[PDB]
Image (cartoon, rainbow, N blue to C red):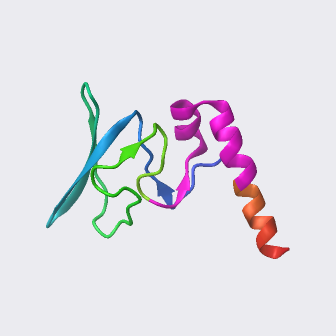
């Protein structure tokens, strides 16, 4: 159905490189680009997938979880989401043999 999940992971809108900022009542991540960049707020115990300073593709999950296939489609293009969709279905079926 292409629903945007509840446990939605937050992907990156553009190319860039990250820098964590873990203060008490906020844990924000910046994916900075050679021009300008955006800031991604999220609850603190959220589980990262970016070692600070690493290099991210546009649409590459920063948090973990499921990916809104729409946020993906707009970010990385059809074969990109065509990819996610096929593999993600399969992981369920494999799991049951």
The secondary structure that dominates the magenta segment is helix
Residue drawn at x 81%, y 75% is: 96
Q: Quadrant of the C terminus?
A: bottom right
Magenta stretch, residue numbers: 64-87
Please say if 48 is above or below 18: below
The answer to which of 16 and 42 lies nearer the viewer is 16
- Residue 89 visible from this viewpoint: yes
Residue drawn at x 45%, y 46% is: 11
Please say if 85 is above or below 48: above
Residue drawn at x 37%, y 55% is: 50
Residue drawn at x 63%, y 37% is: 80
- Residue 1 visible from this viewpoint: no
Magenta span has 76? yes
Please say if 18 is above or below 38: below
The location of residue 32, given as percent across then percent down, is: 26, 37
The residue at the far right in this view is: 97
The answer to which of 61 and 8 lies nearer the viewer is 61
């Amino acid at each position: 159905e292409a629903r945007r999940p509840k446990a939605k992971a937050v992907i990156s809108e553009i190319d860039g490189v990250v820098r964590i900022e873990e203060t008490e009542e906020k844990l924000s991540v910046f994916v900075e680009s050679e021009g300008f960049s955006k800031e991604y707020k999220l609850p603190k115990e959220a589980r990262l997938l970016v070692k600070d300073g690493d290099y991210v593709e546009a649409g590459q999950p920063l948090t973990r979880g499921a990916i809104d296939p729409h946020q993906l489609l707009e970010a990385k293009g059809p074969e990109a989401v065509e990819r996610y969709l096929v593999e993600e279905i399969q992981k369920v079926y494999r799991a049951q043999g």
